[PDB]
Length: 44
Length: 44
Image (cartoon, rainbow over all chains, first blue to last red; front, side):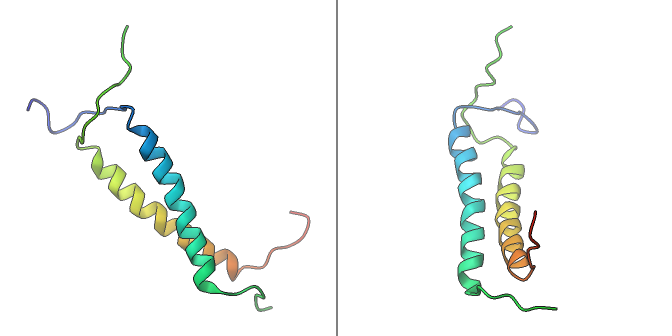
């Protein structure tokens, strides 16, 4: 409408962004350890 | 001088958000599997 190229804005929506970002990372980690299904790691 | 940085919308900044969200999830998963196969020394 005026400047589609750029336009940084930090509205109140940040709540969902910050919460989603943190939750997302936690979800990935959990799944990784879950799928692994291993408690006794091998020894070199 | 009045700059709450308000602006609830979907600007071009989405590029970084979408890319960061996907990359973040991938980072968490990798670390999880890495740490799982990585022993943990005591006194750390």
